Amino acid sequence: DGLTPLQLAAKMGKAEILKYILSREIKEKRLRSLSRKFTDWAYGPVSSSLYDLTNVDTTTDNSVLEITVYNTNIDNRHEMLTLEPLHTLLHMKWKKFAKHMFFLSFCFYFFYNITLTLVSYYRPRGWLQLLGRMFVLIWAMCISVKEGIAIFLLRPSDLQSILSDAWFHFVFFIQAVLVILSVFLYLFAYKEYLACLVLAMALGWANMLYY
Amino acid sequence: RRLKKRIFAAVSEGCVEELVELLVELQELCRRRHDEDVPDFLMHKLTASDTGATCLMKALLNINPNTKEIVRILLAFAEENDILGRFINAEYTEEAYEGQTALNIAIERRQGDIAALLIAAGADVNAHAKGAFFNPKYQHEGFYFGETPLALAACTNQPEIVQLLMEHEQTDITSRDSRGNNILHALVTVAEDFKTQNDFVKRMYDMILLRSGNWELETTRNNDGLTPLQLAAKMGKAEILKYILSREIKEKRLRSLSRKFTDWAYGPVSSSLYDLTNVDTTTDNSVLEITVYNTNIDNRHEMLTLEPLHTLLHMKWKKFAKHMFFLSFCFYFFYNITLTLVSYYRPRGWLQLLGRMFVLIWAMCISVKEGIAIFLLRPSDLQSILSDAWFHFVFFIQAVLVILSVFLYLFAYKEYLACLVLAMALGWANMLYYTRGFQSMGMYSVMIQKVILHDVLKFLFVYIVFLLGFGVALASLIEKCSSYGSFSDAVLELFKLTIGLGDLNIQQNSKYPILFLFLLITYVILTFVLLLNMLIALMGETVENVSKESERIWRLQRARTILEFEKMLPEWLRSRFRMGELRLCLRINEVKWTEWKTHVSF
Amino acid sequence: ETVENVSKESERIWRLQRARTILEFEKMLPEWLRSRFRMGELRLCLRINEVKWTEWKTHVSF
């Protein structure tokens, strides 16, 4: 299956073996390349070290951090993530860019829901609702194609039965296809568009709790 | 360029033949001189240029089990070139590790006999490792020990090296660092507030004070002006505070250092005299004031439950503070009663002025008192913690409300009734603060604060999203002419439906009544069954966490009331100190039955 | 009973949800402007530093 023993312990969830392998420190010479934790200096309680990242980073295709985060059939994932050099890697990758990207996506979804509510409320039962209706249309198209790719990538259909993050992709895709179907029914002659618009508007605020 | 790397690898390897052959090579290099200078060029070739580390320091960072001959012949090589006097006190030059000598690393690397050889060869003990690493901004950014070799040997649990240092003549014990802290402050900052199986720092502080045998170590204020007792009170160190506040030593010539003179004992009944040089509000800054107004600790009740703080708070309570608290409660009760009578029995005169003047003057007094108490609160960080930051705000808001309403009554505007009735509605919710006096009521008045700040605000921050979403989703599809008129009415109907009033009639003026009924049923299932009962379960968890514990917070609220009323008393008629001198020497007596039972039981 | 079983534990699940958010946004970043690797070679050799006060307390306490 193309797995390093480190990756196999990460797949099957073996905390003590992973702790030993991720911090392997041997002092005597001619056994130095086997070690992975070169300690630089120490002064009482403050110490500083160099860890190896041959597998424990997302630079490769399959990797230890990716396996131990996307793994679902174990129950000691926090006990495996709370140890170096996975924890500070997640922390540095958070405070480098991911906080800014999360806040950006949150502001875009907030503006999308605000314009959807204003369009679906201040309706004459034009000249300004197109300015904003195009934005709702293009961000609905973006969200549905993103959720469609993320669902079609979910091939084996077994990870849905576990709680972790299998629901919000479905609800985002359902809201996007609802607002797309409602603007199509508005462009056609049928006046049953109000139900499929108001269901999208009611779901668009229950989407926000994910943020 | 070649030799420096060779001997720096040789001192890390430990091969002594390489050491002596580069020794005689450098000796030939420094007997045939290029006529620049011998000693500083010897130091330049021996030491690194970027960091300042010596071969001695590089040997000491890389301690091998055969380093004794290495350091012996290295100091011998420094002796033959008579460079040892300005060599053994070498130090780093970078700004992070500035001034760190080889003696510090000899002490830190647990090498007692090597450190004894280092101090025997004439090292410097008055060093100050004043780098930015040694005193960082916070705790988890470095290692603080007082940048003194004696203090480092103290905090790193090396009592024989402490004994070797305090017997030496040049080691000035009370020398303060860049922070202004001596060895006792260093031990307090190192000390741990959890009673483990062993605490070396208390025995270290004990033996250091017993070896010094005089009061100048205890009395030296730091740069922030703190006794070590006050520093332990500031940082919250319970065992160190317990040892210092009851220090009892029996043998003579160590008697002035003690603070607990026991008078007599008879079985379990004992009687003692404690000292009150710092543990009283007579000074400006003080231990009791610090350990009560301290906010960033969580063992304040464990620090207050020990003598002579507890009986001092008890005596200061039952002397005057109960009477002053009851007096303030009666005045606030009369103020609220007259405010309610004035704001109720209104003709929409001849008697409401008699009482309206009293409301006006007590409103002025309360607002200027709360304004002084808020303007004294300068740094604006203590508000984020629960303790007593709210009631000053609510008292000031009620006072400015009743003042603004009587001003609007004296003017021509008739919008005064809202700003009067808000003051009247707030004046009774103010009264629950006066339920901190009893025991079975303060634990009911702090639970409102805990539940409001933890659960109800979070639940409303979630629930407002559902309310807005379903309010727009129901007010959108109502065909215009009914009941679900606009957004400012559908949310009223949904709040009535959430609290259990109103109606759920299907016959509405909509285009899709099945969809309208489905949205209403989804809202009732989402909030009436799921969310509100989940809030009830979380509030049950909060009440279970609080009611086992909050006697501590009631005692703390009462102690803050003690110190605030004592500050409110003036210096005139403060004839309520404790005891004449023997140093005020407060007298207590007590019963210790269980320790007496276990001691007589053997 | 369910809320009592969850609220003592679910900090783990919040940390796990945040870590899944990290890796999903890192997958959403393209290879272009992925100049955010860790450290030059010495094998990438990531450098950390830390404070271990309690094990230091128990070790210096003997």
Image (tube, coloured by chain):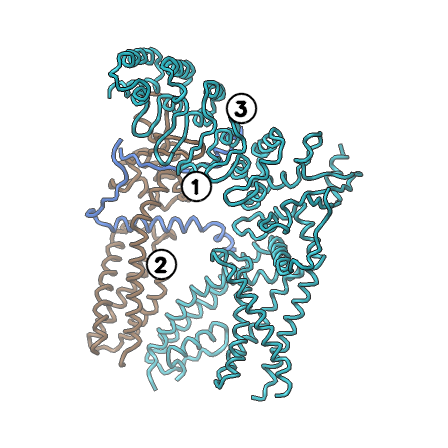
| Disc 3 versus disc 1: nearer the observer | 3
In the depicted view, which residue is nearer to us: B53 or A125?
B53
Chain assigned brown: A
Q: Position of residue B68 (x, y in %)?
A: 43, 15
Whole-angstrom CA distance, mark 3 to mark 2, is 66 Å
The local secondary structure at tag 2 comes to loop
Q: Amino acid at mark 3?
A: Glu
Q: Is residue B244 above or below residue B10?
A: below
Q: Residue at x 55, y 49 (%)?
A: B298
Q: Quadrant of residue B101?
A: top left
The verdict on a common chain for dots 3 and 2 is: no
Query: In front: mark 2 or mark 1?
Result: 1
Q: Colour of chain B?
A: cyan
Question: Where residue B505 appears, x then y in whole percent?
Answer: 43, 80
Q: Quadrant of residue A122?
A: bottom left
Residue, disc 3? B169
Which residue in the protein does label 1 denote? B140
Q: Which chain is blue?
A: C
Q: Residue at x 35, y 31 (%)?
A: B93
Q: Where B554 falls versus B498 (above or below)?
A: above
